[PDB]
Length: 233
Image 1 (cartoon, rainbow, N blue to C red):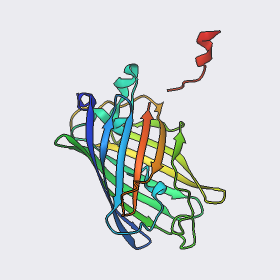
Image 2 (cartoon, rainbow, N blue to C red):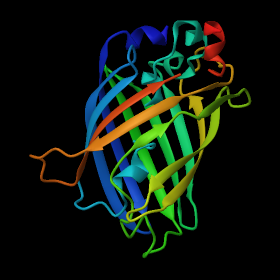
Image 3 (cartoon, helix red, strand yellow):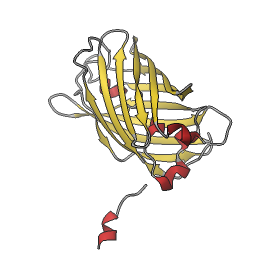
Image 4 (cartoon, rainbow, N blue to C red):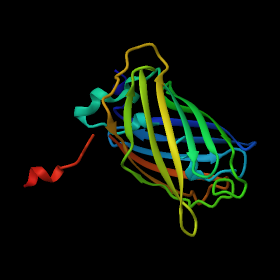
């Protein structure tokens, strides 16, 4: 099925068109993903100058089909099973005491390259807030508690989760995510049982890149792993 499209290294193209409080911007990303290891290596650049929003706020928006699903859970990998036709990934991201992002992305194969084409709209942001004021630390993090549930009404997936962006000089800016995914193609997709995704992201800089950019390394993998110590008495 679509899982066989992720047996090896797959090129990735990411295109984001954003508009936050009237500030329009465009981000392009290139890299590769190895679903066998859940590994993502991507370099995003701003094609419109200095970003009006911090890079960490765009991480979740800027390809969960590269998540490492264990062998016994491949029967519930909706993201890969929707390929190559792909899926629509929609999100609303509420930044606590600030504005919100509304994103709609189409994730699909275009040849041998997996493309994530995104439209982002942000409203109600404070000019002196943590987002428009660039008060967030430039770093990623690990979020091991992301519950993916089946949305049989839309024949896809829904999920809600909180992202915690560290504020410079202390504090945490919360980003409440509400996500739904629906297949683009008519073909059968694997409606999953409820499970979890664990993601660790590392944000860095290319020393030879002059444009506003983000060097991005991410490991993402897919159930209740409690009680592992039971096997060892």
